[PDB]
Amino acid sequence: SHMAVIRIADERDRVQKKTFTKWVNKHLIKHWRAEAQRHISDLYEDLRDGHNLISLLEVLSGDSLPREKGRMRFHKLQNVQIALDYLRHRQVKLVNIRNDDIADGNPKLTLGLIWTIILHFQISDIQVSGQSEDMTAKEKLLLWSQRMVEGYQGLRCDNFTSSWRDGRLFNAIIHRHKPLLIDMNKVYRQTNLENLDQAFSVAERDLGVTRLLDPEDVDVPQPDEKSIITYVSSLYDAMPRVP
Image (spheres, one colour):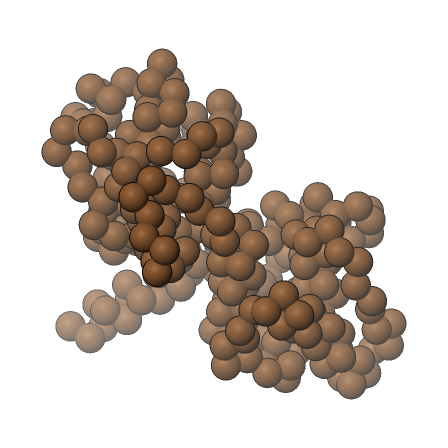
């Protein structure tokens, strides 16, 4: 039923919005200016005037950016363009996004923009042995993921969706780095949620990785790709060495 597919597609979007919202908040709070340490309530509303966008880029780059102090739409578009122009200076190719779209809270383009920023700042230097230079950041992260669970019995990482549903990969990657923290023998028998909860809990408590995903989000036949990548990438950053 087409109704089933839309249901799943809408669900993946719900998860992506929740994920990017947590990711943005994670960084915004690290901003040096107290009043810039804002909290996003609705990703489709709190980036519209451009201020949080500028703050996000400042925190991620350490670079200082100007801000319009007016309230006219003209000021908002300009505020948004400051952020968009910085990304271009950074040689980031902007996909299909206009000032107007961000100023009007365009859902898809807003998520698209946050995705672009995540990709550029968090998934820009993955290094993995066996790496082939032509590979994209996404392809590199997938190889790193595969390289990481290499020596584990019967578990493959064919992608950034279904492959991560049962929590097995998440636990193996943690174990690979801190075996004394994960009982791999037990992760094979227990439920998907059980594995997901454990992984996210250990990652946070012992590796200091923010819990971007809820086990309930990932235990679906096709988890949201970008949500998975985003979190997996933050797992990579918690790793001290390169496989």
